[PDB]
Image (cartoon, coloured by chain):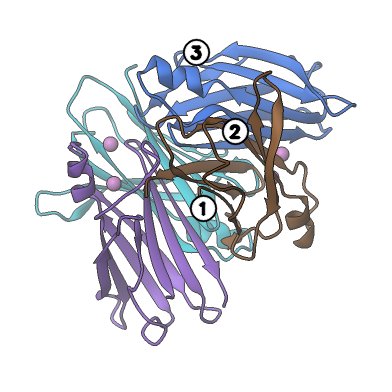
Chain colours: A purple, B blue, C brown, D cyan
Amino acid sequence: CPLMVKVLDAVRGSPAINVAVHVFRKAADDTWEPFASGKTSESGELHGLTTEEEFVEGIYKVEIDTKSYWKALGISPFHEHAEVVFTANDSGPRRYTIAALLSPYSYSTTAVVTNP
Amino acid sequence: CPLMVKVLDAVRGSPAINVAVHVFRKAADDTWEPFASGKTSESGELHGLTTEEEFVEGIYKVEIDTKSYWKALGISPFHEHAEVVFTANDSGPRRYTIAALLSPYSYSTTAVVTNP
Amino acid sequence: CPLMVKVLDAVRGSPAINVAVHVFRKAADDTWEPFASGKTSESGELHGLTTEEEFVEGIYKVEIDTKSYWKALGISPFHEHAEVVFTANDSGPRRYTIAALLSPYSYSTTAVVTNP
Amino acid sequence: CPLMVKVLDAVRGSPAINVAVHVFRKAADDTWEPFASGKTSESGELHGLTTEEEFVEGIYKVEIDTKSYWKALGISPFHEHAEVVFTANDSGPRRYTIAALLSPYSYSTTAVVTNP
Ligand SMILES: [Re]
Ligand SMILES: [Re]
Ligand SMILES: [Re]
Ligand SMILES: [Re]
């Protein structure tokens, strides 16, 4: 419940299905440790990355790999990786939605952060 | 010139060229009155809409004829047109740049106000 | 189920609660007829505007009035109305989400259009 | 100059001034190599990053130090920095303009490619 990633295609007005998502957390030594991963559903969303027990304060990186999405559309992408880096839970637990909007020459990302 | 409009196409990664733009100003009876109109240049820009003297404080609406633009490129888009409203306060001379970024199912608009 | 409007605040990373939403449909005579209305919930979303029986093909306008949201934040907005106009159901029934992202000097809107 | 970066602040409706920008180029071993860096001017622009000869085909990452920018304005933002990737193909001379629009919880990036 506390972390959900959503990916949308601005050209098609559609969810982006089968986008690979990787989450890393910055460790003590300043390296990126693996945290969680998954693939977006039919609705362009990925739920169940983590639990409130595991999603502690820290610096997180969310990566998306869109190759499979673009190729399913018959598109040969010129690049296919996007990353965002943020601080989480630093004023207490919140629920986070990280949304990306894709097009060929533009990219947006927005975070919505709510209470219970 | 105190008012410029700039339009960008996120599908082509290009200025949006020859796009029709209409600017309206809210009248005292709450109707939108025509103010100026034009078509974007080869750089995606439209200047010469107003002199400094004609550009008074008020609530302005910029309407961008995205429908015709996308259809001319063989694309059937979502919106009939793109619209943004912006307010000009009274001030010393200020330049207002209205920037739109277009995709077939999404757009974003920003008003940049600078003291020249 | 077929039409949902969502409004988000990009400054705060939050849903925009109590935003008034009005939907109009273009009639035979080219006037805008009232269609539906409501207010966004805690989650920034408004569901239950219409039913598949009523949401027929046509040209629709979705208006938002953000005054109550901004004033609750202690903000005195310089304008507080946004509109989008689109064609619906023209290739068969779809579900539509119309999302707006607000900030003081920018505005985005995106439509996501899916099947069952 | 064939590469320019432009950064806009959606909270203030202004160019984002004195913002640090780093540009990296992907190397043959898949690492990001430093390419150039600078700070935005009073118009929100950064030019002089590269000569035409140094700007070869490749995959480029533009990192914008949004964290420091927002903190300097008294705002605690979501992202540690903003990142966009763009690819340059081999071609006749082309100008690449990378445009970012910043809010504390959202940003959008676009690559505009023009034939001068
Ligand atoms: Re991508
Ligand atoms: Re404004
Ligand atoms: Re608004
Ligand atoms: Re690109």
Which amino acid is tagged 1?
Answer: Cys
Residue at image position (30%, 76%) is A30
Residue B32 in the image: state x and y as whole percent: 77, 23
Q: Is residue B34 visible?
A: yes
Circle 3 is placed at which residue position? B41
Residue at image position (19%, 31%) is D89
Q: Is residue D108 left or right of residue C67?
A: left
Give the camera-side residue of A39 and B19. Answer: A39
Circle 2 is placed at which residue position? C60
From mark 2 to mark 1, how far is it between C-alphas? 16 Å
Q: Which mark is residue C91?
A: none
Q: Which mark is residue C1?
A: 1
Q: Residues within 10 Å of mark 1 (few under 14, many from 20)?
A: few
Residue B69 in the image: state x and y as whole percent: 46, 18
Residue at image position (40%, 25%) is B76
Q: Which quadrant is the C terminus of chain D positioned in?
A: top left
Camera-near label (2 vs 1) is 1
The vertical placement of D17 against C72, above or below, is above
Q: Residues within 10 Å of mark 2 (few under 14, many from 20)?
A: many
Mark 1 CB in 8 Å range of ligand 3? no
Which amino acid is tagged 3?
Answer: Ser
The chain containing the residue under callout 1 comes to C
The chain containing the residue under callout 3 comes to B
Which amino acid is tagged 2?
Answer: Tyr
From mark 2 to mark 3, how far is it between C-alphas? 30 Å
From mark 1 to mark 3, how far is it between C-alphas? 42 Å
The chain containing the residue under callout 2 comes to C
